[PDB]
Image 1 (cartoon, rainbow over the protein chains, first blue to last red):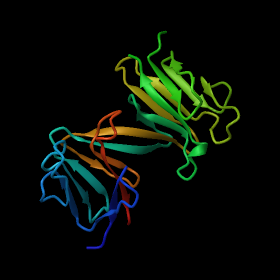
Image 2: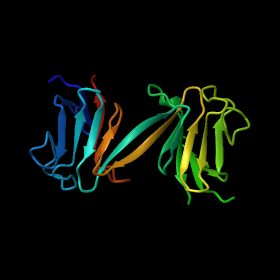
Image 3: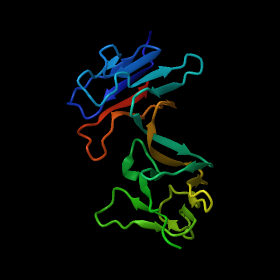
Length: 112
Length: 112
């Protein structure tokens, strides 16, 4: 099955290869059976999570099956709408993917 | 009224002051009238967005009223659940704040 996505391990030595997702379901875990395995990492659950692409809608999802959870850093676009704000979120009044020099970002933190 | 939260401009010289939110509603825009104004920035709408804390629930919200939107970076925790994935999202199988040496992060990108 043709690749619909890829993964790149960050902070790795120069030349880190991409992992191509050529399956409808991609498992990640400490167990050697997973598609992406981390048998020496004690902080990853046996079956930590799975990435799945929907054939019909075309939407990609990640489902956590670990004992402590999976964290995901995400950029959300709020256009003429309301949105929750939690401590740690960064507000970009101006965001440029190509040129972050022009970014105007603010870290929000509650004091309560 | 006491400060319930604060904002910090990122990427600035050392000594950047936190902006204290002392009002239930805090407007942000190019207009000089806004609580947080950017009169010289042309990429910021007259009234860009508004930050609010519910007197009742205590929840904090950011409402966008700009012409092109407001971007928010999020640190989401997925625990025994599902969640959409978008190109640019970073999956942290292992997350240690301030201890990124132990992080196991993968940048996700769609090919289709």
